[PDB]
Length: 270
Length: 267
Image 1: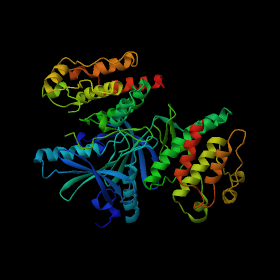
Image 2 (image 1 turned 135 degrees about the vertical axis):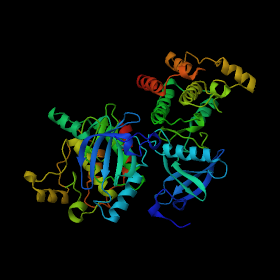
Image 3 (image 1 turned 30 degrees about the vertical axis):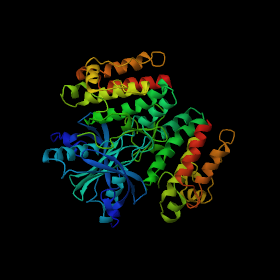
């Protein structure tokens, strides 16, 4: 417990009280913490940019965090600060007052009821506005999945990358370019976005291996072989947007402005 | 000059100035394009070594460093600040799409009032913005219709083109020469809520001079809003913010809570 420095605001560790570890990754630990200047709860991610990364990875991580902290959008989880202290990159992130789309899905399932189409567009047209904004700054999301999508008591969607909310907390959708080449680009995000549009409508991912077999899973991605959504519940517009996003060739996928445009016209159509 | 993509938003080499869009006491403001991503930006150039004493320079650098940490959808984002060419360079979120000043003039010329529902829609966003700024202990210092931007999608952005921080709505604590504090933002906020409903400032007059203005402010003398068009909730919020005594004005948390409840029921 070092002394407060109000003049530093969110840019020093002395102005936070760590509560407990809530996550650990390849290069990082994540903590629940409280800001001591205003009592706001945050996520404090500590990245070992000197000890666990080569020189290129460190310079790329610092550039990427600097961009993420410039995003100002209602549907993106805030990056409030990034600063070097104690030989680590310290990142201060928002924890939203919202549950994951994963929980919303698991709940609608254990109560056997489909998420209605006019709702699916509700959320999806917020997830799209989020991903438009990130792609406009040349920021790739890299892991779009239900657990990273948060949803406010009020129906406000926050896209994040920690899978952490304030009170409630092989990548989830494997693209062809991941499977075949370990490739990830802007169009990889669009594949995942399509898979998530599907999972909201189906209540499960498009792709499962037979008896959970990982080879069977790769064969089903290569054929884009997923059970069709029931058409009496979902328009051609929707099932067609899925089909456009879940295309093995990333060049042939639509860019996030097209998908966001479709998700705006459908959100006003109802 | 030579592009420097390793530097990001932190050198003048990664921007092309397009045109000048503002002039303040200590600063010039440019529309610019980031050459790394084509994102349009505002570029403010602050004369911290020409026009200021050492005290004002150090206050300006401290304040810009705290403004740089604000992050809220209804606040203009400060992307970067750095010293180059012997000036303090600030790269900021560009709105330039529309502002409450233009929206008020449009309704005026069309001889129509802003529905109360529309007032709360824009006002709750401005209250969210200021509640963020106040929670971080940052005062705005120049709240007026021209600093309230509106994006093409109807999103409010509270900015400060000219850096009028560091007036449109005369406050009692400029008449008394007392000092600008967080309650001085609340007076402006109430004057701005009035102006949205009336399409003119509470103390505006056709033939307006310093004497009459002072008298009016001393008496908090402004024309009542039409109760036929604006609710008791709207007219009483304006009345408690437009209070000579800063210590009796509500804090921004109160004003935001009222705006959040008035928006939810009128929509």
